[PDB]
Length: 141
Length: 11
Image (cartoon, rainbow over all chains, first blue to last red; front, side):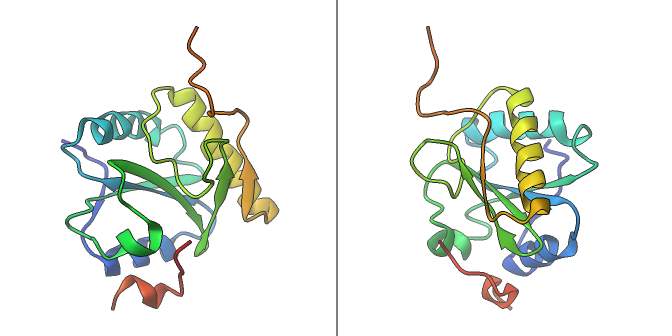
């Protein structure tokens, strides 16, 4: 299904990124049939109407639009990137790299916190923000 | 036009 809008080419991607001025643009790069992307898309669909106020979500198929792979280093199954007014925002998740997500989380509540923190940091002007939790460990006990 | 026309740059 994936009723969320999909972007089919770099032109559409850039137009969508530049269209918004006061809402964070979320992009899920990956193949819709990969189970990791399936889980991520499920969560994003759940949170769409919750964070409609200050965020807009979009999905890109890597095969359909491969131009961004080299520049944005899209080689993992699924990645999530955040943009605001044509600026790429970084997040200190503690995983080692602050550019993308690159894995699938399962807690929509934490995803909501990430969106809120990224939006707040972008409005405050920071190009890099700090997530309110560290993912360096999988916190399994 | 490619994604470079956006004025963006890879990290």
